[PDB]
Length: 284
Image (cartoon, rainbow, N blue to C red; front, side, top):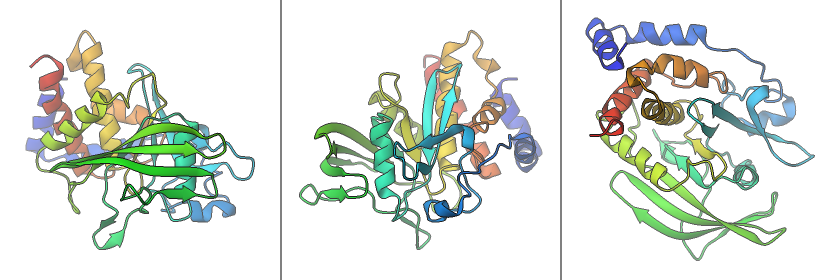
């Protein structure tokens, strides 16, 4: 069923909450035993959001290999993503260790450091060229190289140096700064524009490690980003683009991390974004 007609049908009947609860009921349940070990309590932002054991990213250290992060591997679309929580005061060094070890080119951030008057993640990158950051627990240095501030997003060039080997790499930081404190955006136009800027940079392409994408919990806005990207790519690749079923793609992604898409409003917004984005994919 053409999703655009499926959309109007759900909208006229006002059944978004019913559709969304069906997804919650059919979603995979896999163990997350490592996340729940007592030694990892201060490595998790939210008690009810954990990576599955089978898909979690492991840090390359013998001490404690745990970070709240998951590998989402989409086989037909030939795309992979790492979805993670916003870093905590005690995990900023782990976060940049993962970026280094997984050979990522880009980091995608979909929240502000403060929202609703509360801290949603640590200030984990430097704000001035001449004030670099050193992460002593993981032996990394991070420097701000340049910043481009636009109306709806900011893009930063960063240098990450492995102090053990003195290798350096350029990392691109894509920061969507205008998602509202409550609800979802009224139009998907600026979110889609942002997605295309990330694509254009090479950060989603197979010559690099998987992009790292996060919000506060790494499941809601973060799930909207990867769901929209994968659905648009499948519509490009298949003979019949109307065969792409966004609910089935979301359930496939939920095999790799729990809770992706947090509200019925986020589900509707994902539909809207794919419908409007396709009016470029096809050829317009």
